[PDB]
Image (tube, rainbow, N blue to C red):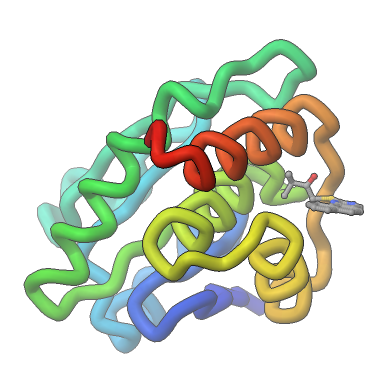
Length: 149
Ligand SMILES: CC(C)(C)C(=O)CSc1ncc2ccc3ccccc3c2n1
């Protein structure tokens, strides 16, 4: 049922239904969760098992996700530093969460935007398109190449 896609051995991508499989998350040694929605609950919050961060974003043609990139990168590095996995999820098409993942692959693994997309698309086959998010990833790639971010 639940597919917590490992983009990297410690970085996982999923949707709303994936984020509710508590046993798999604990078996995968996940200790950090990034919820990239305004309206979904922080699943399992009252159990005190994970560190949470909500990026309150919608899946629209006007939503600004670039503003949250640097905040999400620090949370991922914090999980990376202590040997724990991080799950980033949103909803069915994983448009929002896949944008943050690709951006991290561009920033921390030095993948190009295109190669990062093919990397994620190969492991997570169902990704809904968002031209607004594609444009932001393109602007982010140029800023990386110009050493501006
Ligand atoms: C941004 C987000 C991850 C939410 C998506 O929009 C995925 S959907 C899609 N569909 C057709 C494409 C064709 C070329 C391409 C080059 C670079 C990056 C993405 C694409 C591409 N992306």
